[PDB]
Image (spheres, coloured by chain):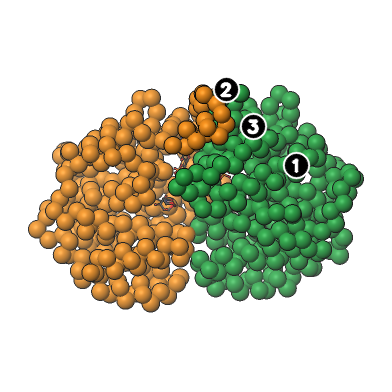
Chain colours: A green, B orange
Amino acid sequence: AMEQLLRAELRTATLRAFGAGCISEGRAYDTDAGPVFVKVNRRTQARQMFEGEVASLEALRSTGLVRVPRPMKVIDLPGGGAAFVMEHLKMKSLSSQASKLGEQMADLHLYNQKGSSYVDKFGFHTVTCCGFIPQVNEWQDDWPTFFARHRLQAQLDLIEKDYADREARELWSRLQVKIPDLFCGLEIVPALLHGDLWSGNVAEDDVGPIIYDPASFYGHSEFELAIALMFGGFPRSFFTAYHRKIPKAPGFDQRLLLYQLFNYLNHWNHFGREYRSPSLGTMRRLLK
Amino acid sequence: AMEQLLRAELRTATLRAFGGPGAGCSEGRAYDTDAGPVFVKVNRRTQARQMFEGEVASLEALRSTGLVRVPRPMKVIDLPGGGAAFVMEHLKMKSLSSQASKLGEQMADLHLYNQKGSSYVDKFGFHTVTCCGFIPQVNEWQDDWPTFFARHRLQAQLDLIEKDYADREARELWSRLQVKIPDLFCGLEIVPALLHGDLWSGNVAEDDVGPIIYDPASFYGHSEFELAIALMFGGFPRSFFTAYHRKIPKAPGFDQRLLLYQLFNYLNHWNHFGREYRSPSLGTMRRLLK
Ligand SMILES: Nc1ncnc2c1ncn2[C@@H]1O[C@H](COP(=O)(O)OP(=O)(O)NP(=O)(O)O)[C@@H](O)[C@H]1O
Ligand SMILES: Nc1ncnc2c1ncn2[C@@H]1O[C@H](COP(=O)(O)OP(=O)(O)NP(=O)(O)O)[C@@H](O)[C@H]1O
Ligand SMILES: O=C(CN1CCOCC1)[C@@H](O)[C@H](O)[C@H](O)CO
Ligand SMILES: O=C(CN1CCOCC1)[C@@H](O)[C@H](O)[C@H](O)CO
């Protein structure tokens, strides 16, 4: 993949990714009680965004299965927005701890089935944000319904409002009809998700892997992996370890396109028309 | 300010900033290598290589002046499955602050370089296509700056807006505005000036040695165009503009031309990001028509 190509093209033995951001400003500070990490966002919806991240961090931390920063405080800023203070963790990009993270992510997804966890619907107890965009987490018994309505339709409604894109509307109407067939008659079980498991949101230290910047809800376990695959950066051993514990159910490859579609639509909304072509192309591929 | 607010909320005397860049953005990714750090941009669309070649050409034109620090382009790689990656030198960088007045001086020198040097580019435009963001621009050489700008910047953006949005108000306001443009340029000498082309605050930075600028979309234009995007989204210290205008003072009619150049950037933002930018685009046209 991209990293092997870079090593070859640049003729370098080492190639360690770095591991602030597109959404919020981020800075570490030393304080009298030790280091902290602070995210700042000046938009009006900052507090909602950070409160969703606090809720997500707390939900993951309650499982005891993965290491994530402790949320400390959400502070309103004069002049608009908010700051979010959390535990500082010394970190480097994910490399040797990839297979351990695959194990942990599979255990996290399986926790709702095997732990003392009783969540039998999809969604979440509070609003979480995809980036800047507030999400509806209203509980639903049917995962394809929840995902179609509260993830894909929400993004395409925003595309319609802001871009008024005819091809996106027309393709979505056809894709809506196909979505149930992609699920192969499977019984989907709710799985607690990190929700934004891009390679830039995972890392490691000497103890093991670390994950951060979650946007959590109870979803289909497979949705977690789509963004990890589409932007790369995870070693193969991450997926090997994960699928040893959660094998690919039938139709996985086609659902992967559906879940990657969501992320393309989200990037179209956050980052503009550069992401129109992969959004439409993915829909067309699903409709072929 | 925000750091006093953190000291109070956390009840700490010290609040000492520290630490590295991190993972980052749709912008790209940084890597440590055997030859030092690199930064890699990736775009999987079929036009990725054209886009990055425009950026390399822009970086090379700026580096040739020796007046401003930009990352050295290293390689453009065709990606399996379509698109390309662009590798350049990595620079450890912070937001522009202490080096703002130095950057103002360099940017003025950059704009004066073509007029004052030996080899003189005597038209507006560029020898290759460059993208301001993702949309390719036409850089066809033109003797007359208001012609170049109206045709290959404003009309190009408005044609896209007509194609994709069929916006009645934009269409009618452009029919009225187009004829008024020459009034903003009469009685002034406009010399082609090499521009960075996308100098908003998010494309400039600094390190211990001096300021750095990057992500250019270069062409030969009216020097004032450079400043429109810098002003309109803020983020530059006042001393940047003070130092700049000590060397190139604001010519008569500067504030009205500033609206025209800001209009271009608003139209470009509408084509990139949608209707959130319709209101400033149309309103800027109305201001110009009053
Ligand atoms: N708790 C932490 N302690 C130390 N460093 C951190 C911590 N959280 C994040 N970082 C670093 O700072 C970066 C900020 O990441 P993140 O919070 O995910 O971005 P963001 O502000 O939401 N904007 P975006 O990247 O577009 O999502 C990460 O790559 C890490 O390198
Ligand atoms: N040479 C460099 N070395 C290190 N970091 C860099 C370098 N160039 C850019 N960056 C970082 O990457 C960010 C974006 O760089 P930029 O050239 O503007 O990317 P971009 O792809 O054009 N952005 P986008 O329009 O969203 O795709 C900067 O804000 C820096 O943090
Ligand atoms: O920003 C994120 C990851 N993408 C950044 C742009 O380059 C590709 C990876 C995630 O935090 C998330 O998918 C979304 O962008 C939040 O808006
Ligand atoms: O992204 C750019 C600057 N704008 C980003 C949204 O906040 C206001 C500043 C530039 O690269 C360019 O002027 C154009 O937006 C296409 O990317």
Chain ID, mark 1: A
Helix, strand or loop at label 1? It is helix
Residue B214 location (% of width, % of height)? 39, 40
Find disc 2 in the rendering and name its residue: A32
**Which residue position holds label 1?**
A60
> Can you tell which of label 1 and label 2 is closer to the viewer?
2
Where residue B159 sits in the image (x, y, percent)? 37, 69
Chain of the residue where label 3 is placed in the rendered structure: A
User: The N terminus of chain A lies in which quarter of the figure?
Assistant: top right
Question: Sequence order check: which comes first, mark 1 or mark 2?
Answer: 2
Query: Does the beta carbon at disc 3 come under 8 Å from ligand 1?
Result: yes
Q: Earlier in the sequence, mark 3 or mark 2?
A: 2
Q: Which mark is residue A129?
A: none
Residue type, label 1:
Leu
Q: Residue at x 70, y 66 (%)?
A: A149
B281 is higher (above) or lower (below) than B6 = below
Amino acid on which the number 2 mark rests in the picture: Asp
Q: Residue at 64% across / 47% down in the picture? A: A51
Choose top left, top right, bottom left or bottom right for residue A190. Answer: bottom right
The quadrant of the picture occupied by the C terminus of chain A is: bottom right
Other-residue count near label 1 (Cα within 10 Å), few / some / many at <14 / 14–19 / ≥20: many
Q: Report whether mark 3 lies on the same chain as mark 2.
A: yes
Q: Which residue is mark 3?
A: A87
Q: Residue at x 38, y 39 (%)?
A: B204
Residue A283 showing in the rendered view: no
- Identify the element where label 3 is drawn: strand
